[PDB]
Image (cartoon, coloured by chain):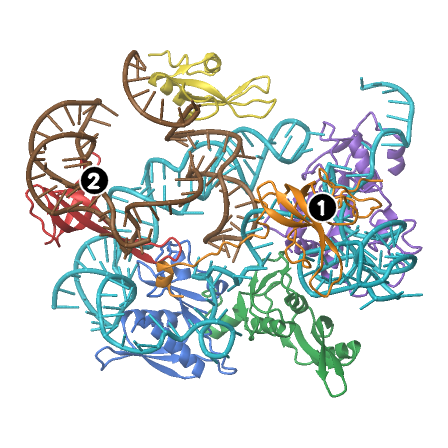
Chain colours: A red, B yellow, C orange, D green, E purple, F blue, G brown, H cyan
Amino acid sequence: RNLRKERIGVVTSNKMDKSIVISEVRKVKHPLYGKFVLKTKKYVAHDETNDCNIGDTVRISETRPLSKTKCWRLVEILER
Amino acid sequence: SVKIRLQRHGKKGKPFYWVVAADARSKRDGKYLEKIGTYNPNTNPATVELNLDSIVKWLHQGAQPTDTARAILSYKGALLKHHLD
Amino acid sequence: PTIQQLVRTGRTQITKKSKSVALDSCPQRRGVCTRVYTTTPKKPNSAMRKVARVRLTNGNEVNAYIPGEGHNLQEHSIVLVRGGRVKDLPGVRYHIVRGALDTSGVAGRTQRRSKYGAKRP
Amino acid sequence: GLELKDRLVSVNRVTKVTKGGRAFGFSAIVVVGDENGVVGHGLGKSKDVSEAIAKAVEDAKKNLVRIPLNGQSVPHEQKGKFGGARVFLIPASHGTGVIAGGAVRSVLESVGIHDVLSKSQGSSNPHNVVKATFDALLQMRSAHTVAKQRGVSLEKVFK
Amino acid sequence: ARYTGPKTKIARKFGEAIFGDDKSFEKRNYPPGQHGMAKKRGKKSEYAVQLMEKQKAKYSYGILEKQFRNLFEKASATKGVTGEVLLQLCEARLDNVVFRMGIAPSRRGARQIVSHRHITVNGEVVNIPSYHLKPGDKVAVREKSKSLEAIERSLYEWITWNNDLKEGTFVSVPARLQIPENIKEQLIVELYNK
Amino acid sequence: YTDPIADYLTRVRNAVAANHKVVEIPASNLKKEITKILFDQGYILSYKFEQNTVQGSIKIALKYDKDTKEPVIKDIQRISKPGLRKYAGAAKLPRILNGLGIAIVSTSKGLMTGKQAKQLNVGGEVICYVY
RNA sequence: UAGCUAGUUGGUAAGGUAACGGCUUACCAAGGCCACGAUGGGUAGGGGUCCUGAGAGGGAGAUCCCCCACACUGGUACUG
RNA sequence: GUAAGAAUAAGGAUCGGCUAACUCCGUGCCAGCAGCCGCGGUAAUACGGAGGAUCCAAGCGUUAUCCGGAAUCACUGGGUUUAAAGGGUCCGUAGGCGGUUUAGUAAGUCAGUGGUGAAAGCCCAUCGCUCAACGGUGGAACGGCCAUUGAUACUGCUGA
């Protein structure tokens, strides 16, 4: 295989059918002042039985595009 | 069809060719795949720097040499070596 | 100041407003004159400087200063403005090339011949 | 030293207003150095230029200072302010040259430096920039001096 | 281009005979001009000093400012003493070596003999005066113009010159402590870094 | 506080400026490591780790010459700050005082000097520099 | 320039395309983005690179090479 | 390669200070010059001409657009009593920073390996055009990104 990309994030909202949206925070150094800045990005993952709720810590992996703006799936729910 | 051809890179009056494998649908001295050898027809011996470790590899992969390419690869080897099955 | 303040809003760099603006950022511009007259400096100089109202090819009305002595510069003449203001006439911010299409050069000039458009005697 | 050469940095004409008219006067700054180890600056005030320069060099002949100039130039980088000016001296090589300003060049040529880079990111007053260069040059201590002050051999300060 | 003018004037405006210590160096040694013969300006600026110290070397060899700056920034690529390598590459010129070998007693004659296919360098004839002689070159004289009238008429520590075959075997690149010249390279470096 | 390391350096700098003899700084592992490094490099005379406190004290004796005192600590400043952390591998270490000063670098092995870490080819975070 | 989006956001079945996919259709829910700058306006092809500068940076994207868009102004399909 | 013949070939800018180079003649706040200071009202080293001098050189000056000098937007590398600059004062949201010790992970940080970072271009070294420009070869660089293996001193997270 090839071990497609994987991210770890926090569930932000569950208001859709069989789909969740999580937010991932990363600390990147500023290109000029060299100060580490917390930048956020929101992914859209795929859920089957609607198990995770807002405030959890999930781990998603990149797959084929299952829909528009939806190319991830939750596999490794860690904390609730 | 990937072909083994020559790319002109010298100066005005004195040419200097690179024996390189490239796609036929590309410009002469532009994009290529992998530089193979080097040809300098500025001295009497007509110096060459062929690389028989990749020439036969490209020939097996499906390269198609031209007249000058197959005349440079003639008196430097890799043709009597590509023939051996 | 603070690194956090700089990260939020960095240093603002100004644009350095140019000097010669009404010539479209070209070295020379052709133009036609409409009024050739004379003006006074501010102080304490006392003279009669020769200026001309030139309408450039890009639709700009400027005031050019005629260098040297000796010229025709009628009410309608094709001149070539190059730029370079003077600190005596308020408003004149351009110069006219001597030796251009229609403007005359100078006679009896021998030292600064490259300027004022004078041939070598 | 004994073979002291002088150099006039700047001569400025001053004026004092009185009831009658203007009372002129000349002030001169002269840096005199042995070109090897010692240098000193002085100020002279008079009415004639030659008398002012003579008083300046006679006052600068006193209070000479010794400066370490390891090899051919300064041992390390140093800053000197003395109020208005702000001079920064950095050693370069053994063949670079003295890249200095207007008044710093005379001081660096009179003290005996031949390859250094000095940036004056401050005022342009000859009265203050010479003293700023002096303040930046007197704070320099060589490797032997720092080793003796620490108490460690002269190999741990390098390794 | 070349100077092609009076050399005594150039010697007088610098106070040092660089084209041969001979006639006219004395006898009004003061600089030329109607205002140079009189009491010149006393206060001489450091910029004037550096500029004249550069022009002395720029006039002694016959180099223009363009080529001099090119050679300076070429020699400045060496990590050693910049002025030292500058003077070394300026001395390594072909016409300068021909002048030092005894032939063409002046550099102005060196850059008129070398530019006439009268001298050969390592076999093939080289008629370029700015030719940079690397250490270990063999300079000879063309056999056609070998028995000339001026060559035998006109005929160092690093040049091994042999008069029997017009040899000279340029080797052992000299140093500042060996090249005799009354010029200060540190001033030239400071002027070009100004 | 905002930077105990900055306070530890500031107390020493102020005492040196005021021509004191001993300082009674609070204690911590990082301050003890910095004190050990400084004593090994030869910028302080002696140091004592005083107990009988909830945190503990560090009593450091400052060094001056026996004539023309001229304190050996002329400039002791920080490079990394809690508002801007500056790290560097074993190629971008500073050149404090042209090799005549020390630069403390917290490395993956421990607390070392800028010159003692370049030999080990380890990077780390530059904490402070002393002339 | 503080609200924007209504096939828009997600799902269930079909039609499909070389190929997954609101790409399209039928049905259900109201979702999705936004101060870490949506939306709106002005300008602009992008990069390897060029100039300058001690460096950090700043200013441009000719000629050489790679990618994209276009062929009087617009739309559509066939052959392959 | 052979044969007459120095024959077939030097100009532009500047000269009060910045900035390298000064004397005279004519005009008398006029004509004019000028990048800034600014010169000319009848003894002008600043205007025009002549002589001399300086720089560059088959080029020399002006204009237009850029970088440096400008530490004059400052992370490197500035300030806020009187020169421009502390909000009229508190509370507090988002955010920024974090007293001591200890256990765990290793996200930031550091080190190694593999892949990539096209060619061309800059730099270094070496060869061919009589040298150079130019061209060939090699190295360095491409400060970056992905995967993996280690260290745990400092920051982040969890527990005490």
Q: Going by the image, does E137 lie left or right of A76?
A: right
Percent coordinates x, y for residue C97 in the rendering: 70, 44
- Residue denoted by label 1: E65
Chain letter of disc 1? E
Percent coordinates x, y for residue H119 in the rendering: 46, 31
Of the 4 image quadrants, the one containing the N terminus of chain A is top left
Residue density around tag 2, few if under 14, some if 14–19, many if 20 or more, within 10 Å:
few
Percent coordinates x, y for residue E117 in the rendering: 78, 29
Relative vertical location of residue E189 with respect to residue F41 in this rendering, above or below: above
Relative vertical location of residue E131 with respect to residue E59 in this rendering, above or below: above
The answer to whether residue E75 of the structure is visible from this angle is: no
Query: Could you tell me the amino acid type at mark 1?
Result: Glu
Contact between labelled residues 2 and 1, with CB atoms less than 8 Å apart: no
Secondary structure category for the residue under label 1: helix
Residue at the farthest right position: E27
The answer to whether residue B10 of the structure is visible from this angle is: yes
- Residue denoted by label 2: A69
Quadrant of residue E191 within the rendered picture: bottom right
Q: Closest to the observer: G2 or E40?
A: G2
Of the 4 image quadrants, the one containing the C terminus of chain A is bottom left
Gap in angstroms between the C-alphas marked 1 and 2: 66 Å
Percent coordinates x, y for residue H144 in the rendering: 36, 46
